[PDB]
Length: 48
Length: 48
Image (spheres, rainbow over the protein chains, first blue to last red):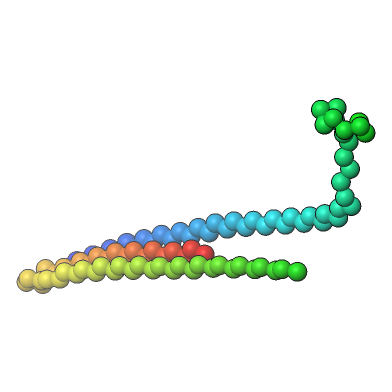
């Protein structure tokens, strides 16, 4: 004499992305010409 | 002149799935009935 029905459908979804980037550049141009010296009194040299 | 270039890359990917299902039914003297159930689980992972 009677019929009954029930349904229950549940769903879940999840996504997660993490991105990290890093860059570094270092340039050095070294163009020497020479060295200059001064004489300290402790050296004992006549040019002081 | 001296140039040195080094490159490395790693890719990892993982996937897991798991589905469960169940069901039941029966009737006596027309007093019928049924039931059903389900469950799912999907996990992914990408690492670069």
